[PDB]
Length: 36
Image (cartoon, one colour):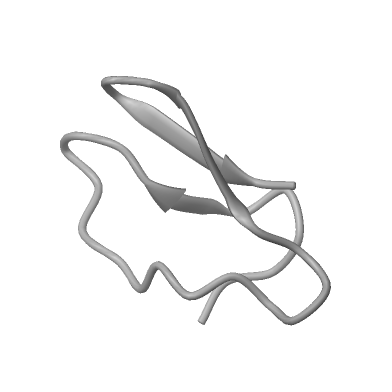
């Protein structure tokens, strides 16, 4: 899981991607996705 303002995705990223309830995953760019 990931908490708010948490990088849930993004190239080079190697971690969980499920945003904590209440937030969703927003792909900022092809190398970063923050949960907001």
